[PDB]
Image (cartoon, rainbow, N blue to C red):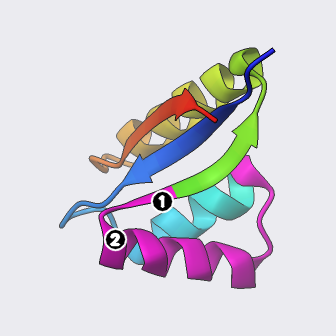
């Protein structure tokens, strides 16, 4: 039954706007909440985008990666047990 948290890692190439876009897009964040998480990731090196069931966490990871790569950004996204 364990839920899984989705994490994005900081990097020195992915635009902030794209990270905000990603959080609004795939994690259902208002722009204000996205901005907060984006800045937290920038400062902490890692941040939680959300917590979901394993299957849903898995698709959100893939979707962020797919989106990032097609935008040609190196944005790293992964998950771990909540």
Out of 63 and 71, give the one closest to the viewer.
63
Please state if 28 lies on the left or on the right of 4 as rendered. Answer: right
- In which image quadrant can residue 61 be found? top right
- The residue carrying mark 1 is 47
Please state if 14 lies on the left or on the right of 66 as rendered. Answer: left
At 80% from the left edge and 57% from the top edge, which residue is drawn?
28
At 72% from the left edge and 85% from the top edge, which residue is drawn?
32
Out of 16 and 7, give the one closest to the viewer.
7
Please tell me whether residue 45 belongs to the stretch shown in magenta.
yes
- The residue carrying mark 2 is 44
Position of residue 82 measured from the top left corner of the image (x, y, whole percent)? 64, 36
Please state if 67 lies on the left or on the right of 27 as rendered. Answer: left
At 37% from the left edge and 38% from the top edge, which residue is drawn?
69
The reply to whether discs 1 and 2 touch (Cβ–Cβ < 8 Å) is yes
Secondary-structure class at tag 1: strand
The magenta stretch is 26-47
Position of residue 42 measured from the top left corner of the image (x, y, whole percent)? 34, 74
Out of 12 and 3, give the one closest to the viewer.
3
- In which image quadrant can residue 20 be found? bottom right
């Amino acid at each position: 039954p364990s839920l899984y948290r989705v994490l994005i890692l900081n990097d020195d190439y992915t635009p902030m706007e794209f990270v905000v876009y990603v959080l609004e897009r795939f994690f259902n964040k208002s722009r204000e909440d996205a901005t907060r998480i984006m800045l937290h990731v920038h400062q902490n090196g890692v941040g939680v985008c959300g917590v979901y069931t394993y299957e849903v966490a898995e698709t959100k990871v893939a979707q962020v990666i797919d989106s990032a790569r097609r935008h040609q950004h190196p944005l790293q996204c992964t998950m771990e047990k909540d």
